[PDB]
């Protein structure tokens, strides 16, 4: 078979996008609880009722039924985040919140009960609001300690229940979304490249430090980074556009180069110099970065981009989704190869999927469902490209479909753009029964997993 | 100052393309002595008078004068090959030929007397003809032994005269030029991909072996590979074209990957299976390759190439590039692109060991009465490419130096002709062998002198 026998098939969410129960069992407020309009929207002074993340999909209470569905599809892996504000409500507590730790104990146990391995993102846009408001988030080096305290607590607690960990979901998303991403509550107009890059530096050092701690705790742990995969193509063979495209890709490669190689790459100096960025290193930083680099690289992949040296563009060769995003399955094979060529370490595709406004409708069998042939087609083409990449010799640990049960979106905090194999009946206004339904893609994907990919051909 | 203080500035030739003196001082025949039409041409059973390489430019005798010219330009480096057949005429002798070793001792000595570091290519398309005939060259594993015998011999002899060594000029040349590059005697139509890749495997193993030996002899030696650099661009943003371009570049990356990384790369498995290639490893091969990898990567660069998943809708002309009189497209930015691609992949120092512009230079008298060449085309080419090298240095790429190809006009490899000239120094000899063989400073001589002496500062 093309797919390895140990290949991990699954789905992925973030805690804040599903759990709800934002006020329960001593959970402190996160940044997401003041973001009713999502990452692109403004923050409220206090949580408001129209914020869908308060309730989410109520995964916090519904996880056993949900996990039953995951199990019927045959997942051997499930990616989620541990919500930081559940373990350390303010973030500065001397002791963890035991009800939080107990909750995740139960979650993981339930997963293992069905033969499903947890894959845990330590920080996924969940920063305790107190830390954000008090320290302005990651612009403050004190965040490292807080994060360390968080990580250790959970690494130790779950050390026999969780093999796979991710430190940060895209450290560099701090650049576009300082608040959601870095818990930085200073207005974007007031943030220099210097402050943003310094904040990302603190994240990278924390990632390394936590990698060290992890390895001391359990030598069986696998610790990955998580970055945005976006292969870039030149609009034309004009060498000026080829070079523009290279330079564009370096923006992203900088952070993965730190994660994997353990030092700021050769081209950083120039860029920093041209952008007035000078990273302030604490004396321990270089050695932490160099000595503790990631075991694997995980990434989100949605689309490619086309670049030009002209004072990117719309690729005329790509189809677009009903929602208006272009679609590029070959770009997945391309970026898998680019990353592998560059780093020679295992890769994990941890976010991929097709968003659409699915409509729940009774099929001719009387079952309420979503006829999403579009999602089946997207997943199929992408996974065939994954198969090509496996044959190219790229090491790929697995694939977790993004928002495998419909979740609240990160960017807008809406439910109507749906990624899931499982439809959840709850709407943008908060209404609905919260019942779950299998989409047609549920059955197809079940088939792919149970055949370990052979059904793709 | 943007160029490092220690930057190496110079010129490059191969022995067979300049030296002449093909039968002198105990020299044995090389494969080049039976290639009067060059690597693209047929081999002759015995050397023929129409072969320009018999006399070359007679660098063998005139090297002191030529080197005084190199020194007037301010070269701190000069790249050539040691002709294998001057050391081991047949290749299988128990003892080396002392007249040849003495010759290179004297050559390197003049170089150092003028403050020029030698850069020595161990094998540059010069395999002793005896070995090519007897063993059919690199298809036979015994070549490893002979090559090793040869390299140790020179590595030891020159251990205090030569710091920088290259093992092979393009191992993968074998694919296109089995006889010229691999000493492989067998008719081109009778050679499978399997045989060629096996020959190349032998070369790679031999390169690692010699790397081990070099390190035992002198820990200050720096050993490097030499590959063809050819950055590829997709004709359109169609991801099919982008993938076709990626695939194309892997053909080349395979060999540099073994040299630098020390193992056959991940995509090789698929490519080999599709092409009926199965490499036969000796028991110690994999560990040798893994443990002894090059200190640096050196390359030739002339041009980029554009690729399409479907070429017949139009190995394609790049609309945006200028072309030389001779008819090659010109792509300076491509040099920055490829320096960065290599450094991104391997993170080791790079060395540009072949670059230049070929043209039919006309020797004509200027207004000062001096016979010269008005080669401003060549000045423009070098200026633009060296400005791209400067960009790459600012990009943080580690670059050891630059050696202009055929710095003194030399016999070409592909055609064995003199009329297409790369040099800063014109040599009067023509395709039919005629002429005085006198040397003349081209206009580019003075300009390049100023570049070197300012350490690149004159480029700005």
Image: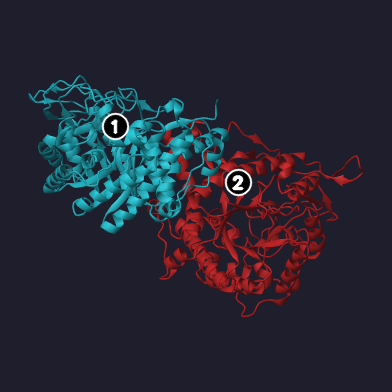
Chain colours: A cyan, B red
**Chain of the residue under label 2:** B
Which one is nearer the viewer's eye here, A407 or B73?
A407
| Residue drawn at 74 percent across, 57 percent down | B52
**Marks 2 and 1: which is nearer the front?**
1
Can you say whether B261 is above or below B95 in the image?
above
Helix, strand or loop status at disc 1: helix
Residue named by callout 2: B393
Q: Is residue B261 left or right of residue B321?
A: left
Q: In the rendering, at what x and y percent does residue A316 appear?
A: 43, 25
> In the figure, residue B171 lies in which quadrant?
bottom right
| Residue drawn at 81 percent across, 54 percent down | B72
Which one is nearer the viewer's eye here, A322 or B375?
A322
Asked if residue A429 shows in the view, the reply is: yes
Q: Residues within 10 Å of mark 2 (few under 14, many from 20)?
A: many
Label 2 – label 1 distance at C-alpha: 43 Å
Helix, strand or loop status at disc 2: helix
> In the figure, residue A445 lies in which quadrant?
top left
Which one is nearer the viewer's eye here, B239 or A24?
A24
Q: Is residue A437 left or right of residue B19?
A: left
Q: In the rendering, at what x and y percent does residue A345 appear?
A: 37, 52
Please tell me how many numbered marks the rendered image carries: 2
Check residue B308 in the rendering and tell me which mark sits there, or answer none: none
> In the figure, residue B66 lies in which quadrant?
bottom right
Q: Is residue B217 left or right of residue A44?
A: right
Q: In the rendering, at what x and y percent does residue B79 appear?
A: 68, 59
**Chain of the residue under label 1:** A
Residue named by callout 1: A31
């Amino acid at each position: 078979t093309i797919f390895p026998d140990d290949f991990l098939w699954g789905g992925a969410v973030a805690a804040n996008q599903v759990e709800g129960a934002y006020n329960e069992d001593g959970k402190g407020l996160s940044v997401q609880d003041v973001l009713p309009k999502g990452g692109l929207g403004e923050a409220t002074e206090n949580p408001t009722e129209d914020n869908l993340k308060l309730i989410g999909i109520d995964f916090y209470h519904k996880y056993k039924e949900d996990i039953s569905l995951f199990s019927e599809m045959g997942f051997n892996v499930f990616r989620t985040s541990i919500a930081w504000s559940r373990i350390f409500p303010k973030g500065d507590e001397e002791e963890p919140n035991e009800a939080g730790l107990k909750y995740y104990d139960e979650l993981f146990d339930e997963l293992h009960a069905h033969g499903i391995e947890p894959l845990v993102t330590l920080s996924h846009y969940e920063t305790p609001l107190y830390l954000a408001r008090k320290y302005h988030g990651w612009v403050d080096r004190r965040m490292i300690h807080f994060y360390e305290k968080f990580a250790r607590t959970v690494l130790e607690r779950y050390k026999d229940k969780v093999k796979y960990w991710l430190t940060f979901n895209e450290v560099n998303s701090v650049l576009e979304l300082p608040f959601t991403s870095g818990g930085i509550d200073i207005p974007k107009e007031n943030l220099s490249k210097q402050e943003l890059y310094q904040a990302i530096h603190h994240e990278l050092v924390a990632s390394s430090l936590v990698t060290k701690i992890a390895r001391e705790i359990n030598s069986e742990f696998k610790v990955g980074c998580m970055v945005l995969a976006m292969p870039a193509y030149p609009m034309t063979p004009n060498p000026k556009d080829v070079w523009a495209t290279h330079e564009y890709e370096n923006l992203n490669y900088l952070f993965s180069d730190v994660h994997v190689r353990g030092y700021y790459p050769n081209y950083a100096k120039r860029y920093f110099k041209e952008n007035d960025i000078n990273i302030e290193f604490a004396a321990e930083d270089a050695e932490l970065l160099k000595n503790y680099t990631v075991d694997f690289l995980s990434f989100s992949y949605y689309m490619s981009v086309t670049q030009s040296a002209l004072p990117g563009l719309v690729n005329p060769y790509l189809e677009s989704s009903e929602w208006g995003w272009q679609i590029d399955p070959i770009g997945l094979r391309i970026i898998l190869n680019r990353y592998y060529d560059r780093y020679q370490i295992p890769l994990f595709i941890v976010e991929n999927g097709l968003g659409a406004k699915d409509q729940l409708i009774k099929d001719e069998l009387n079952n309420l469902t979503v006829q999403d042939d579009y999602r089946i087609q997207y997943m199929k083409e992408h996974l065939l490209q994954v198969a090509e990449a496996l044959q190219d010799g790229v090491e790929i640990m697995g694939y977790t479909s993004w928002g495998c049960i419909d979740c609240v979106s990160m960017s807008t905090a809406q439910l109507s753009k749906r990624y899931g194999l499982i439809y959840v009946d709850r709407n943008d206004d908060g209404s609905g029964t919260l019942n779950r339904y299998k989409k047609m893609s549920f059955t197809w994907y079940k088939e792919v997993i149970e055949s370990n990919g052979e059904s793709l051909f």
